[PDB]
Amino acid sequence: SLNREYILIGTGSMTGVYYPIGGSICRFIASDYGKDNKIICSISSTTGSVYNLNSIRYSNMDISIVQSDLEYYAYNGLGFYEKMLPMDNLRMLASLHKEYLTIVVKKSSNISVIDDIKGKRVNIGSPGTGVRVAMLKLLGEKGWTKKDFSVMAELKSSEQAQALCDNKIDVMVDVIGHPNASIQEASATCDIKFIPLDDRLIDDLHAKYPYYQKDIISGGLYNDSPDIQTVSVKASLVTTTELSNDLAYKIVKSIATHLRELRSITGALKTLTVQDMAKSSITPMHDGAERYYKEIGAIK
Ligand SMILES: [Cl-]
């Protein structure tokens, strides 16, 4: 019939990074194809990769921005998805920016190494998010549980900057690309520093949790600061085999065609290239996406 294909893209809170990225994708789609009256794209602002992946599982959402941790678990039916069927029909459209496990304190705090966060007021993020998974794994490695902290706050990126500078939390924890506006806000409001992860912790995390890569947040992004050793994951745009070859192709092509605008959406995307988009190490690439990346030589 003459109805447009209605595409819904899971993102996150309007205060976050995913929301404007997804909004931009819908705009690229409208600009490239809107006049042909076959496609209409919308975003969802509900937070969390669990929500988004469940919405995809139940066929009420087509595509979502997620990150590697919950992508890995959903695809494999492991960990938090232990009791569910693997989402074996999940497919990647494009890898996006890296997100780094980022631990931030006031310089005035006593805190210098990871073991100093024990006993403090710390953020563990909202349920169903990459931050929550990272914190559960980190506590896991250290053998720590709720009794070992005075406060386990459940704040989003923006909320943490203010909470940290007001001393309502001692340790901001996020899994985010850099440079990031919330960290910038924090550093403009009080004097902050980053806590690195030690070699053994990074090695153990990468060994146990294949979605975490050993990585470095380069120094000097927000103030005078050193390189910070930590782990990273990737944000990615995922879908399922229910999305047609044609739409997967068209969507990836629209993003690639508008890459220079995408780079401008947030600081962490400035370096993104088509070669970066074409990588997928957890979920198979959608056939229609692969068609595009091969056509332009982003994959050999
Ligand atoms: Cl999330």
Image (cartoon, rainbow, N blue to C red):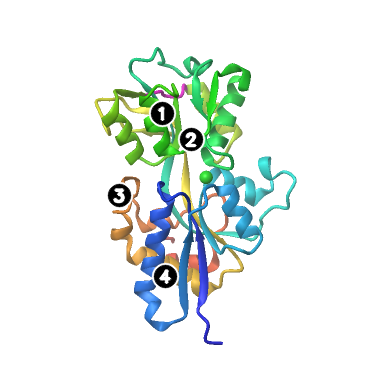
In this figure, which residue is indicated by the disc labeled 1?
163
| Quadrant (top left/top right/bottom left/bottom right) for the N terminus | bottom right
Which residue is disc 4 drawn over?
295
Q: Secondary structure at mark 4?
A: helix
Q: Is residue 100 left or right of residue 53?
A: left
Residue drawn at x 33%, y 67% as measured from the top left: 257
- Badge 1 marks a residue whose secondary structure is helix
Residue 71 seen by the camera: no
Residue 155: numbered disc: 2
Residue 127 pos. (x, y %): 58, 39
Q: Nearer the viewer, residue 122 or 211?
A: 122
Q: Earlier in the sequence, mark 3 or mark 4?
A: 3
Highlighted magenta segment, given as a residue range = 194-198
Q: Residues within 10 Å of mark 4 (few under 14, many from 20)?
A: few
Whether the residue carrying mark 2 lies under 8 Å from ligand 1 is answered with no
User: Sequence-wise, which precedes: disc 1 or disc 2?
Assistant: 2
